Length: 330
Image (cartoon, rainbow, N blue to C red; front, side, top):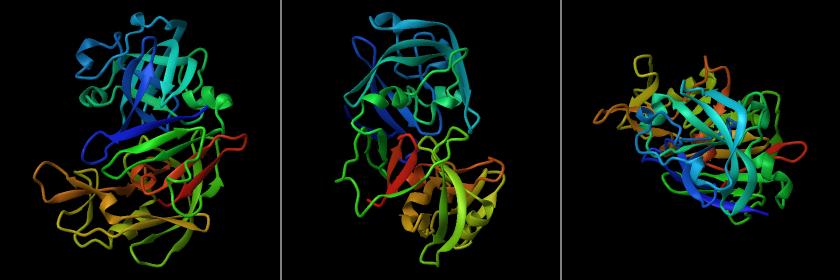
């Protein structure tokens, strides 16, 4: 089997992407944030505290003939941005882009933090990291991908995120029309539960490439590119007037700037992030200070190749017995 679903930016900045997902019988379609940096599929639901729901579409298990309470199971998750959610668990039929998994754990939110409430466009998350990070207790649950894997034509999914435009998540096949040149594969460590890999270096604009190992994670659920302070300083030093602002919470730059590109290495290959992808617009409405899309990972504890980086590439998440990651230009 295979599946193919379109993913759409939630706003004009590509802060996140939503993908329609069918849950239950008859289908209830919710727009979920596919997150290769976590491993829980959770949804706003008929159980979510009413004051914490503000425009989201909810899953109502009592209206699904295939829903079953996973008795005794609870979940609770905290994300890198400080947001969180928790609740109980049902199993139900879940379909993405025509690919169906029966018996998928659907984690029903009883509580969500303010960032989730405030985002009316995101009805929940669908985790695509390794199932070892799944938070369901006392019986840990598998991700949608892990459950689908044995049925897939090939044990892979791909992320093809758009810049200010829709893109695609495919399951079970590589669309050879969706990228240019060849795919360069690189080793993955699953030791922390992430799609963790080592970039071979970087360049700023038309500058020379610096060969240096940068361990980080491929994370579709993080908006920006978070890299070591040395690398980030070298980037922003090429932008007149750019500075790190503790009051704003990162690097800002004059909105009159033209940003240089940023290149990262994948083995001997190179992915170029155009300068425009690094512009996250005014820090507050009408400001002439703009927020940068490349930020320091210092104090996160991990480097994160988030959407800013990933949307410059066609990315293969290879879940074969030895997982790997592939990157191609597009």
